[PDB]
Length: 187
Length: 187
Ligand code: NI
Ligand code: NI
Image (tube, rainbow over all chains, first blue to last red):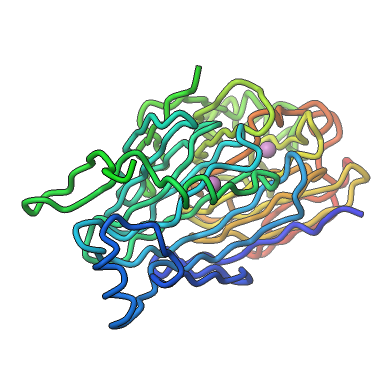
């Protein structure tokens, strides 16, 4: 039986998708992700801010099918490091992804299985091509929510563990009022 | 070798992707597509208007990878029928597609291999899920350009021929200033 085509309204200003399933990620949800563990623990104890919310419209995991989701990445810092999504490689490593930036100031940090990293700045209208094999994490580098839409293969899946254990080979921090992409000491 | 991640600017007001492959389809490129052949012939001779332009960013045809393209679908009618894209099934029939409406007023006509049709209205912010097996054609029902972004599997390809020969089971026309989707009499 064929699946039904549908249209859903995406609000470019809030990232809310009609009919999507919501995911809420708080700072407490990201232990071991930020370099400055003291600032993390302190921020989690004081207020445990929401780091990002995701609104996903996903299909069964099937070759050739497509999922899509917006993310609203909140502004903030853990010590010097800007708020980011957990990041992942795809379970089917060779699956690509396309991101479309809708609101705010941010960027994407990507790395290969071997650790070689890339940084792609994102502003409203920027479309980012995430090639096969690249792990990817988005970072909010501004003062307002950073909102984007992502379209990804239905069978791409997720390898979060690799990133949770070793993180990214680079980190994105604020140094002298400037955004800088630098080596991860933890790496 | 790993492919290079990149970002490109997509302009939401003009639909232009900076540096993408540009394709132009004029009314003369769509012979046999509109029901009113005499009206098609007449408009071609009088003006041969551009019906739509496409800006595509494509990868090699490999499983799990992704292409993206904007379309600028110009307003117009051939007889009573609104301007539309040629439309296709995918060569790998079960490949889905995601459309993001950016500007203007239009919609998507879809149909199964067995001819069952569906119409989905699109206004700015509408995201349409084009499931596996459904042929799909966009239509402009307003008086300004209808602009959208499409993300599709790199290996979907196109089967333009089926639609070229017999068309969609439905057409989108204007009757007494109103937009109507009705049975295609040449189907
Ligand atoms: Ni992904
Ligand atoms: Ni298609």
